[PDB]
Image (cartoon, rainbow, N blue to C red):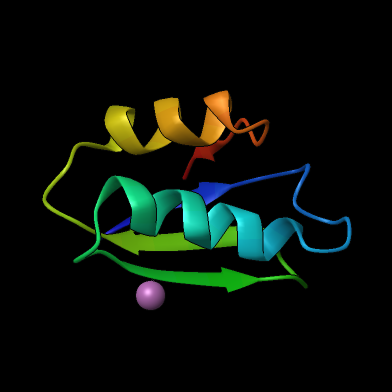
Length: 65
Ligand SMILES: [Au+]
């Protein structure tokens, strides 16, 4: 259970693209996004660095929280 803040997750369709990116990397992951807090909560067997790397490549660099 890992959490990221994504400051760029504000535009139309951005939270969808975040979730879709993570589910494409790990189809068994659980992903919650909150537009009020720009927080993304992830349950996955991948590492936090693997998730962050994927988010970065997608244009949504996170900060782990
Ligand atoms: Au999910």
